[PDB]
Length: 170
Length: 84
Ligand SMILES: [Cl-]
Image (cartoon, rainbow over all chains, first blue to last red; front, side, top):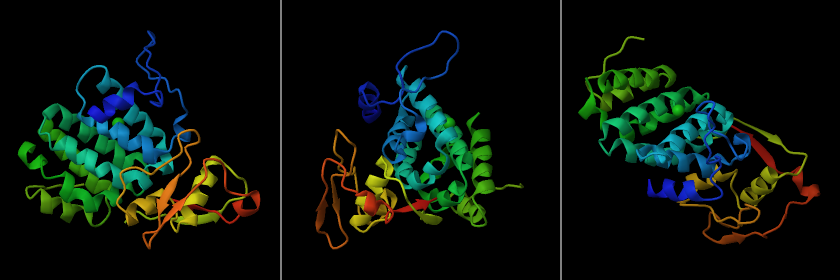
C-alpha cells in the first residue's frame, strides 16, 4: 500500500506509466525475464491491498504479467509472498479478498510445484475465509478447489483443518 | 519445503553469475537459501550495479563485496546454477 505507492513513483518501477488508447495493456520498461523476482514480485504483491486508481490497475496488471511469464522464477520467491497475501486477506475487505483469491488461483498454476509449496502456509492465509465462506462464497470454494487440485496429496486435510466446513469432489 | 530441484555449472560470466558467486562465497546457494537461513528484510546491494554488497555468514561474521565485478572468468565455472 504505502510501500507500493512509493514503488510506483520510483524510476525503478518496471512498468511505463502510460495509457495506450488502443486497449488496456501495460507496457514494460524492463523485460520481465530480466527482473530479479526476489525484489520485484513481493513489491507487486504489496499492492494487493490497493484499491485506489491508478495504483490498483498497475498492481493487478503487474502481478498478472509477472505470474504469467515468471516461469521458474516464481517458486523460489514463494516464501516472501506469504506475509503480503496474509496482510491483504486479513483486512477483511471483500474487494481485496476477491482480487487476492483470483491472484492465488493464478499463483498455484503459475508454475510447477507452487501449489504443493503453498500447503504449509494454509494456516497463515486461509483463516479469514471462514468469515466469508458460503460472489465471494463461490469464489472461496473455487479457490480452495484449485489449491487442492495442485497441492498434492497433503492438500485436502490441511485445507479442512483450517476450513472445517470444506467439502469437495474433484 | 522450497529448495532447488537440480544443479548445473556455469561457463559464461553474467550479472546473474556474479550475484550467484557472491552468495556462494558466503555459503549460500542463492538468495532463496540466504533468506531461509537468516531473517532478512532486504539484501544490501550496490545501487549502480545491483550487486550483492554484504552478507552475513552462518557463523554470524560478515562478507563484503566490491561495487564492481569480482567473479573471475577462471572462477565462473565454479559457480553452481540451481534449478527450481
Ligand atoms: Cl493474476
